[PDB]
Image 1: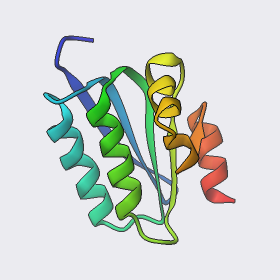
Image 2: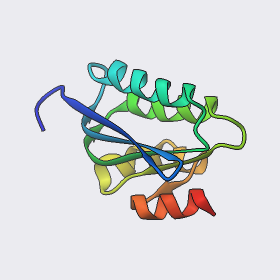
Image 3: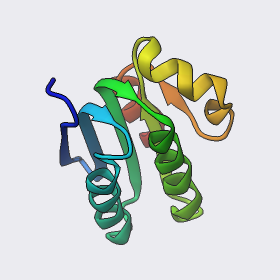
Image 4: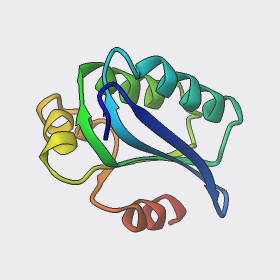
Length: 116
């Protein structure tokens, strides 16, 4: 991963939109991530998973983006976040966001839950 660099991949998995992010989420890269997620949310998917498995640094603005995303989804829209390791899981846990929406250790786990 390069400094101030982000990759966002958006892919349909059998009706579930998966937004997969790599690199670092902070004030510099946040507008790119926000625009990507915003366009997915605007398409009203039946479910949305944000996969942060490949994110090496998750800053505060990234948490704000997760919470704002959840707050604007359809009332019946499935949602989950995938996070592995302390760089991503610790900020989510410290701020209580995993009490607001489901946090999963793998994409497979998230996809199973959103389809049940």
